[PDB]
């Protein structure tokens, strides 16, 4: 129904998905003129993130990105409701332009971005029900840049070889998802926004950590070159690249750090 | 169509199919998509010194302010002669005075001037040209906050007479080349589109490398003088943030400079 490229690309999402042309759209450029320090923004607590290595979690190529299913016993503590995990997934660019984060900082894209999606389990019974409702979603965003090899990210990336094509799936043994978060999680940007893909509902409480994580040049290249958005038997195969939405016009972004 | 709300830029494709098509402008000018082209030679600006005995219509059309230009103003150096039709501006707002259309290495400038031309070797007028490939050529000048600019003030001194949609004022001829920056020989060149509906992908863009300056007071005037609504409208709407977000570009921008 929708794509990141071509005639069904992001400027056309609003035809079928009205909220994509509505208010509170994400992602955004995090820059000085729209920030405000909020001393009340305390560190979140990440509970249940240490997933048992005896359990397995489904990784799927759905044609738009790769996503890992997460159990609802994982949750964020510190918001007005409990938010319980549902999935994590990534957004990236391409080897010729390896700058495919969704959020930018002072107009700069990072190489990639990880989103850990949660739903308000105090108010709603599941993520689908929560997704178009008040206070329904909370997403944690980790900016990713090129640097040292990252063994924790490789716990996902080592499986990309088995989800090359749309509709393919692989089981990933549990590991500590907190390993994917950066140093100093206390420093973050906080704002009310939306899903960054259709249906673009304006129901997401975003937390974008200030500090990026690093993955190696080779890990980033693998992420950018391993996957296809087409089924294996498609006579017109299409590489899965540039699967991020452009920044949206933006209204205040609160920061847990004063400078 | 508008730049904010239900008829804003993510909705333009609902009515204007080209706004969701290929070759859309503006774009972020950054290293990964740039290629030096030693063959790109300086444009020559012919007829830009408009007679002071003549006058040129300035119009608030509800989306920006535009100044009509005569077809005896020409650019030489492209594959055809292109003749002027108008100039106009794009800007931000006082709380976020960063409303250029093009960005450079992810940074918005305060505003941007467009001087629109059409291929007069092939087409009799800009309307005809606008639907034809490379029918149009636009010169873009990036504008930053700095010194007072007496040349731009030859346009800005009139803003208080075109405050509302449909209002018009005459501007005596002056040297339009005074609106251009230093070292016009240095520029970015790419094939793109109109940045407003109908978004036709028919524009040869030239973005000069170097910005010009206007003062904080001049920028504030440009950001606060104009309304998108008619004078008698019971709910006035300020004309601010009348720039399109940057578009995906994955394709090369050629530069006339290497360093
Ligand atoms: N970037 S984002 O964090 O906004 C965000 C989400 F949040 C959710 N998941 C949400 C919660 C679970 C499903 C219920 C409906 C809301 C989607 C999802 S999703 O898997 O559920 C797809 C449906 C929405 O397009 C995605 N995708 C986009 C397609 C590629 C994989 C990740 C997304 F990018
Ligand atoms: N940013 S841009 O340079 O792409 C660009 C153009 F080029 C043209 N003028 C072109 C040539 C003259 C008229 C023929 C049709 C194509 C528009 C125009 S225009 O006046 O002709 C309006 C066309 C609306 O469909 C505009 N506007 C947008 C609204 C505010 C004033 C300037 C524009 F922003
Ligand atoms: Zn996402
Ligand atoms: Zn313009």
Image (cartoon, coloured by chain):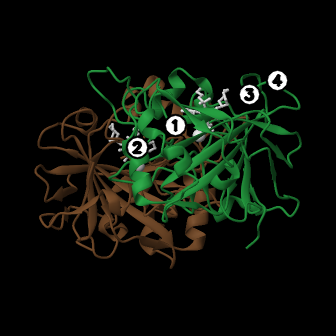
Chain colours: A brown, B green
Q: Earlier in the sequence, mark 2 or mark 1?
A: 1
* SS for callout 4: loop
Q: CA distance from mark 3 to mark 4?
A: 7 Å
State which mark lies toward you, 1 or 4: 4
B196 over B208 or under it: above or below: above
Which residue is under mark 1? A10
| Residue at mark 2: chain | A
Tell me whether the residue at label 1 lies in contact with that at label 4, contact meaning CB atoms closer than 8 angstroms. no
Q: Which mark is residue B124?
A: 4
Q: Residue at x 38, y 23 (%)?
A: B230
Neighbourhood count class around disc 4 (C-alpha, 10 Å): few under 14, some 14–19, many 20 upward: few
Q: Residue furthest front?
A: B53
Q: CA distance from mark 2 to mark 3?
A: 38 Å
Q: Camera-side residue: A28 or A201?
A: A28
Which residue is under mark 2? A196
Neighbourhood count class around disc 1 (C-alpha, 10 Å): few under 14, some 14–19, many 20 upward: many
| Residue at mark 4: chain | B
Q: Camera-side residue: A105 or B95?
A: B95
**In the image, ligand 1 is in what quadrant?**
top left
Dot 2 and dot 1 within a common chain: yes
Q: Which mark is residue B126?
A: 3
* SS for callout 2: loop
Neighbourhood count class around disc 3 (C-alpha, 10 Å): few under 14, some 14–19, many 20 upward: many
Q: Position of residue B163 (x, y in %)?
A: 40, 33
Q: Position of residue A250 (x, y in %)?
A: 35, 47
């Amino acid at each position: 129904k929708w794509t990141y490229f071509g005639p069904d690309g992001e400027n056309s999402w609003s035809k079928k998905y009205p909220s994509c042309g509505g208010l509170l759209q994400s992602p955004i450029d995090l820059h000085s003129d729209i920030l405000q320090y909020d001393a009340s923004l305390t560190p979140l607590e990440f509970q249940g993130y240490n997933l048992s290595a005896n359990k397995q979690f489904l990784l799927t190529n759905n044609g738009h990105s790769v996503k890992l299913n997460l159990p609802s016993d994982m949750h964020i503590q510190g918001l007005q409701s409990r938010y319980s995990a549902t999935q994590l997934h990534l957004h990236w660019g391409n080897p010729n332009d390896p700058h495919g984060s969704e959020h930018t900082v002072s107009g700069q894209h990072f190489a990639a971005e990880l989103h850990i999606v949660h739903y308000n389990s105090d108010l709603y019974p599941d993520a689908s029900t929560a997704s178009n409702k008040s206070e329904g979603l909370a997403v944690l965003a980790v900016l990713i840049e090129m640097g040292s090899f990252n063994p924790s990210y490789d716990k996902i990336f080592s499986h990309l070889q088995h989800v090359k094509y749309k509709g393919q799936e692989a089981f990933v043994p549990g590991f500590n998802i907190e390993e994917l978060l950066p140093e100093r999680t206390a420093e973050y940007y906080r704002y009310r926004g939306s899903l960054t893909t259709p249906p673009c509902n304006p129901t997401v409480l975003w937390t974008v950590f200030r500090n990026p994580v690093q993955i190696s040049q080779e890990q980033l290249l693998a992420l950018e070159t391993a996957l296809y958005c087409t089924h294996m038997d498609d006579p017109s195969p299409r590489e899965m690249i540039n699967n991020f939405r452009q920044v949206q016009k933006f209204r205040l972004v609160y920061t847990s750090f004063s400078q």
